[PDB]
Every structure is written in structure tokens, then in C-alpha cells.
Length: 216
Length: 266
Image (cartoon, rainbow over all chains, first blue to last red; front, side, top):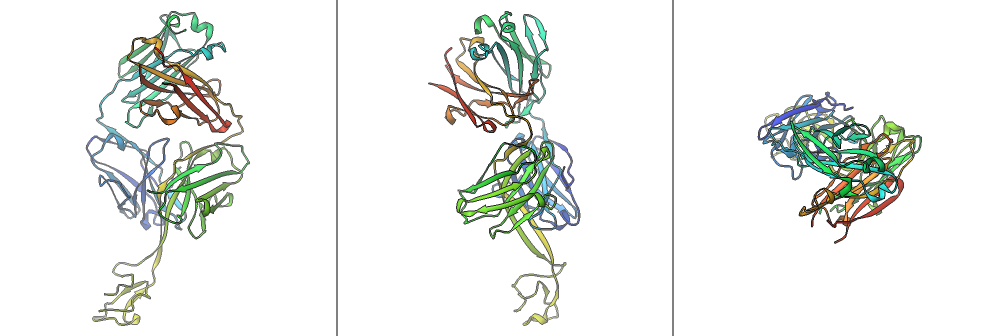
């Protein structure tokens, strides 16, 4: 949820400045001692700011913050790709051992280089095949921006049945990863001349192909 | 160096049970530090749970106070949290953290605080003071004063890693781990891309390493997909030049670990 109000999304461009606000009440943000935190999804937060304006140990002066009455502001100057993250403000609420957080803001940094996907396509393992199943695994990495579409082929037919593809997940380098699984029986796998994973990204397709005759 | 914190506890708890987590601190310069707990539920913001300070005094999120108990054992540098009667709404990543908690005396504009009075003395006893009568204030009565208001400061200094806790009735399924090689798509490649398929498990998470942590550069472990089977699968890959290779897969909920040998020959 989040008690303190933040924009859900903000965008800035590489090398420029962006600001995130944090609104509360006279009894929290209004009292001062606002803090700020940076988090990458799936990872632990990092404290940026405490006491409204003080940078935490080791935080560079690119990050600054301010407060006016019931609204605190975090400003990030000289935006870099590594600043893409979620940002949360916080305050004590009626006690030094009770805290409320902001609703969180996801920062996007525009102007980054486009990067096509790297594609790796793995055939089924012998161990899996020994159980009469064959899972083809298509691993997709280092693409920017974070949108792909995946098409599976077998001997020139498009296969949609028993395909499951993940969302794109931002990696640390701000590029994205995704994976696609085609879940077959061993007979279905062995029936075909070849299978392909075709990954389209910003209108360009990167295809890898495996052949049961080469792979089993 | 620097304090580091590590959460431990179950990755899966059944509804109506007690969730019990432990926070172990290491590497502090200090004898003890105040430790708090924060959770983040899928798609919610961060939510405070509570803390215990170096005097053993606790404070809690008032919304959760009746369900929480935080205790410590400084001889083990540990702090524990218990949350009673959990429901799926308590599924979250749980963090422990060092916290700064301080009560400040706030004064109106134009009023000083502290025992630094300026030719002036005996201002220390007053919370908020001015020596403004026109000359020196030798005694507390020579100063204008008001009573201060109290402002509470809270922030987190250092965060733990975070422990994923699922609250669910669902059964566990340990993964089946299969070795992968890209070899057969390009047998003359200078490098070989190896992998492991961590197939068909519940709940999250799993952890993957390679060669017991000796292989880290070039490793890419992917987020899991939730499949029609109703189970998760994820994969991990590593590229090596054309030596044993082993993916180390742990699934805490099932107390299972598999170190799967992958053939790098191509």
C-alpha cells in the first residue's frame, strides 16, 4: 500500500536530473526526519538519505533531498542506467519505533542504447527424455528496451501449445532477461527435423535452432 | 568491516501457524545495535513490523502489535521475530535491519537548546531558551524559555538480504534438476554454454550456484515461470571456453539440494 504518497512512475533521461516527491501529514513528513531508500526488485534496499537532507555513508552527492512542510523531494542528478530502481520515502509516525513508508516510485532512465537479445536454445536432457518428456529451454538476455515476443517453430509450423514465456526482468546492467519453455513429449521431440526459438525485439528477430538428430 | 545482517527461517509456513524468523548480525564495531524488521508483500510497498533496541525495549507497528513478538539474544548477536496466526496476506520478503531511533526536543523559531549558553551560564536546565533581556544570563531565571515539543526520528541504517516467506496451504514439490548444453546447435563454437533446468517445484525460491561458487562470472540465473502444471521452473546457464562443471541447486522449502554434473564436451 504505502501511507506516504509518491508518483508510481517517473522518467528522466541519461545525464539529466529528476525529482521524486513524497507527501504525508503534519504528524509524519511535516515533523521532518524523512529518509529515502533505493531498491532493485528482488534485492535488499539501500539507504540514500536520512534527516530530510543528509546522505547516508557512501552515497554520492548526485543524490540530494529536501523538504517543504508535508512534502519531501529526492533529486537525482547526472542520471545513469544504474539509477533505475524503485525509490521509497519514510518517516516516523508518532514514535521513534513506528514507521510509515511511501507508496514507492519506479524510475526509468531514457536515452539508453538499444541492445538486441542474446539467445541460447537448449535441447532436452537424456535424463528428462528417459521420463518420456522433452522441455526446450530458450534463454534470452541483454536486451534493451525490455520487450520481446517469442515464436516457436518445428519443421516450419508455428507452435503455441504448451509454450510458457516469462515477463522481461530487468538485469543489473538495466538490460533485460526472459525465458521461454516449450514442454513436449519425447515422441513429439524426436518426430521433427528441427525446432527454433525466434525472438523478436524492436522489429528484429534472433533465431536459434536445434535438431533432434544432432542433439539426441 | 561494517555490520551485516542475515535473515533465517522457513520459506513456507501454513496458515494459522506462527512465523518465526531470526536475524543474525556480524561484523559490527559495536557491542549491540538496535534491530528492526520490515516486510514487502508482492505488489505492496514496504511495511514496518517492529524493533528492539540495545536496552531490550520493543516497539511495533500498532496495526500488527497484537500478532508480533520481537526478542533478542545478544550472546549470539541474534534478534528474533514471531508473527502469530499468519494468513496468505503475510506472504512477503522479510528484512531485518539496523535502525536509528531517537527522540528530539524541538523548539519554536528563535529559541536555542543545549548547554552551550554563549559569557552566559546555567542554560542547560532549559529545553528551549533565549538570553535576550539585554545582557548576560548568569542563572536559568535570566533566560526566556518555552517547553519543547518532542519529534521522533526513525530511519534504517543497514539492511539485510531479505528472506522470501510464502504463507500457503500448498504442498511442497522438490525440483527435478536436468543438465543442459548448447553444444549440439554449434559444435565448432569456441565456447560451450552449459545450463541446468530446475524443473517443476513449489514454492519459490531456489538458489543456484556453479562449482560451489567458484564459477560466478558468466553465470546467468533466470527468474522462474509458473507453468500449467501449477509448478515453477527456472534455468541457469554459464558460458565456459572449450574441468568438472556442476550446478548447485537448493530448494529450502523441501530441504533438498542437488549438485548436478554437466558434461562440457563439444
